Amino acid sequence: KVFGRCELAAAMKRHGLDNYRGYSLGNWVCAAKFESNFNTQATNRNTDGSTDYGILQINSRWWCNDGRTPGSRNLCNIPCSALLSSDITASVNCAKKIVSDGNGMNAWVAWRNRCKGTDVQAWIRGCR
């Protein structure tokens, strides 16, 4: 599923990401925009042999199991494929643990490089 901007905003809010660990909702929408272009089915392989999955590009080394990643810890206790679903519940549940781990949203490279320090509330402009 490719979410619309406000659609995704409303869903992320529903699942409690708005100011989760102090991060305003526009951070999360911006993160999804540039990690996945709002597409829940996005996947991308990484040099260490892991893969990033879903709307927030959650990694198979630490967080989810994809069966082919050396060093896998599966700390969200979930198959990576669950992170590709139209329903973003599993991605949000796992992202909450990621953002809680020590480095906050810096775990998301696209957020760090394209969202962090910007006017992220622009990402929910227009939304009801």
Image (cartoon, rainbow, N blue to C red):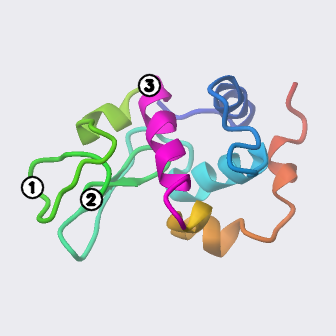
| Mark 3 neighbour class, 10 Å CA radius: few under 14, some 14 to 19, many 20 or more | some
CB within 8 Å, label 1 to label 2: yes
Q: Amino acid at mark 2?
A: Thr
Residue 68 marker: 1
- Please say whether residue 55 is visible from this viewpoint: no
Left or right: 13 as drawn, with respect to 32: right
| Mark 1 neighbour class, 10 Å CA radius: few under 14, some 14 to 19, many 20 or more | few
Residue 118 position in % (x across, y down): 82, 68
Dot 2 corresponds to which residue? 51
- Please say whether residue 101 is visible from this viewpoint: yes
CB within 8 Å, label 1 to label 3: no
Q: Which of the 4 quarters of the picture holds residue 7?
A: top right
Element carrying mark 3: loop
Residue 86 marker: 3
Residue 100 position in % (x across, y down): 54, 53
* Of the pair 77 and 87, the residue shown nearer to us: 77
Segment colored magenta: 86-102
Distance from disc 2 to disc 3, alpha carbons, whole Å, reads 19 Å
Magenta stretch prevailing secondary structure: helix
- The residue at 31%/31% (across/down) is 82
Residue 98 position in % (x across, y down): 48, 53
Left or right: 73 as drawn, with respect to 120: left
Distance from disc 1 to disc 2, alpha carbons, whole Å, reads 9 Å
As displayed, is residue 101 above or below residue 93? Answer: below
- The residue at 51%/65% (across/down) is 107
Q: Amino acid at mark 3?
A: Ser
